[PDB]
Each structure stands twice: as structure tokens, then as C-alpha cells.
Figure 1 (tube, chains in turn cyan, green):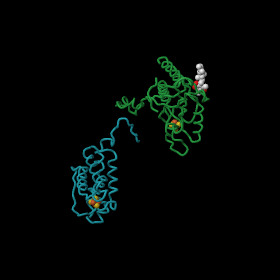
Figure 2: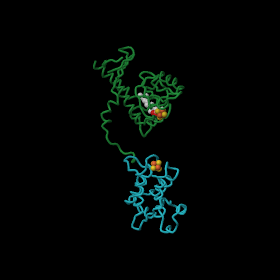
Figure 3: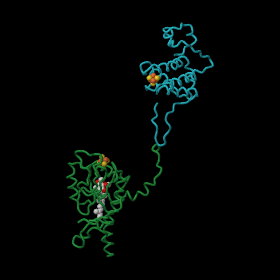
Figure 4: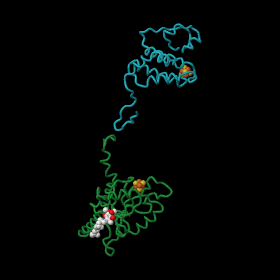
Amino acid sequence: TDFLTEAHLDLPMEFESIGKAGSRLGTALAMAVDHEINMVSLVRNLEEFFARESCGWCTPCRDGLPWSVKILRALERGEGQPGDIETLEQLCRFLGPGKTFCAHAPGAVEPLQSAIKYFREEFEAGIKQPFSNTHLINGIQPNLLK
Amino acid sequence: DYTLTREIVTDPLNVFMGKLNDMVNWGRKNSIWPYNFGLSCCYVEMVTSFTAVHDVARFGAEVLRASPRQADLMVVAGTCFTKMAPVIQRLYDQMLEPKWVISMGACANSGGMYDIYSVVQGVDKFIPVDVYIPGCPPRPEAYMQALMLLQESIGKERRPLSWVVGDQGVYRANMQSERERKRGERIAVTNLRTPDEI
Ligand code: SF4
Ligand code: SF4
């Protein structure tokens, strides 16, 4: 289920009330997160659970949850690179209902998108190195994209 | 080793006759008069070799002739188009002995990149060739290198001294291929300059 803030504590625990708030009622067994919990680490733990509990049938869950896991591991270690949060947002967009074979991956991407929406400053703090996907090959001048 | 035309034979070569035949070959190889014949882009690099920045006149091979009777070397530098092939054959037939042929460029060598309905696949389909130059085009110094190869071929050949005295057969030396001669130094190359610099 999507994370909610302190201001959402006043609405009733019904299906449509939580659904209009941007989350799901789910099992209605709520979990509180205090200020001492890093949201990047928490969402990393959640996505490690969800990626390792993929059944492996369909491509977006099976091959997109581990990418989000690796991005969150890099963000937790301070080795994030530009485009990582954009990749996470696109993963939340493309793992929604109907895109995957079952509802496991939409539930996987609900906390990630909610935490990026509400606690973006913790995710941007993990980006500390420039983007580098290629090493230099001696004798070949790279195509310097702008 | 030698090739006979009138057959693979041995070297036929008195001590005055051998020296004077060597002087004949030296005069022939140091006085080569190419024929002026423009086919395609390879001719542009050939006349680039004729100019001042290369100066093929140093070898004595700048005398360009518009008449095949006064030309000893025919440089087929260009594509052998089907309409031009009888012209090339007639120009080659109009030349006088001794006559040598250098194919310049992939078109003259084999047809090159034009395996097409209107191109003869190489000038050796109908005209004998003594020196082939790969390239498209070969650079002017490659033409000069082929000229030196032709001089080495000329200096090792035996031709009839006169049409009334002696053997009238033409002997052409079966020289070692340049590929096998340069295989010793070419394979030993390890590192080349990187293409990023100048
Ligand atoms: S979304 Fe469902 S069907 Fe697809 S791999 Fe994940 S658990 Fe399996
Ligand atoms: S070999 Fe290449 S450069 Fe020479 S005539 Fe043919 S196309 Fe032109």
C-alpha cells in the first residue's frame, strides 16, 4: 500500500476514503514509520521483498523490480546517478495495473511512488556521482551527447 | 625461374653478350614512356603522380605520349567499361614491342566494386598485365612503387636482341610475390598509432 503522511491520519479507514487519498485500505493493519527511519532504506527493504517474491511469469515485475532494487541500493550507499529517480518513476508508471500479469507488481510499486512523492528529498540525497555507463576505449573517440 | 613466350624454363643467360643485354635492360627500365589514357579516377591519381609534389619525372617516366607507337608502358587506370574495352584492346595492339602493362586500381584489377552489367571484370580478361596495384584509388606513391616493381621486372627479363640474330623468345622472370616477401615485416607489427590523434 502507498505511504501516507501525518495529515492523512484523520480520515476514516474505509475502502473509498483511503482510495481517494491515493492509497489502498488493504488489510487495514497499518504500520507507523518514525523520523529515525530513512525512507530510502525502508523502500529498499520493501522492494527487495517484492523483487524476490516475483513469480517470474511476466517481464515488467520480473525484470523491473530488481532494477529498482539496484537503484535503491545505490541511493542508500550514496552512489546514485542522474536519471535514477526518473527511472524509478517510469518503473512505477509501467508496472501499474494491466501492464503486468497479476496485481503483485502494482502493489510493489505503490510504496515506491508514494515515498518518492512525499519524501523526494531523501531520494535526491543519494545521487552523488555523475552518470557513467561506459568506460573509455583507447583509440575510439566517444560520441559526446549533449 | 622464367616463363617463355613466343612454358616455364630456366635462365638462358658469353660474358660480353650478358653485359650488353644487361645494358639493354637498364636502358629500357630507366626510360619508360607511359601512354596518356584517361579512364576514371585512378587516372587523376596517376597524373597527380606526374605533378610537382611527387615528381615521377625523377624516375624518367614522365614522358606522356598521345601516340601508342611512342609509349612503352600502358597504365590501365580506371574501369573497363564494355564500350571502352575494344578501344583499350586496339590501343594496346597499336603499341610496339617491348610493351608493359600496369593495372591501377581495383576496377582495372578485377572490376572492383562494379560487378555490374556494363563493366568488364578486370582488364586481364583480354590484356596481359605485368603489375597490379590495389587501391581505389591507389595513392600516387603507390603508382611510383608499382613503377619500381616494373623496373625490377624489366631488369630481370631476357628479350631478343635483334630480329635477325639469336633466339626470338621473350623470357619473363617469375619473381617472388610481394606478399610473401613482405610477410616477414608485416606480421611482426604490434602497435599502431591510435586513430584519435593526427
Ligand atoms: S506481476 Fe504477478 S504474474 Fe507478473 S511476474 Fe510478478 S508475481 Fe508473477
Ligand atoms: S578503382 Fe576506384 S578510384 Fe580507381 S577507377 Fe575504379 S572507382 Fe575509380
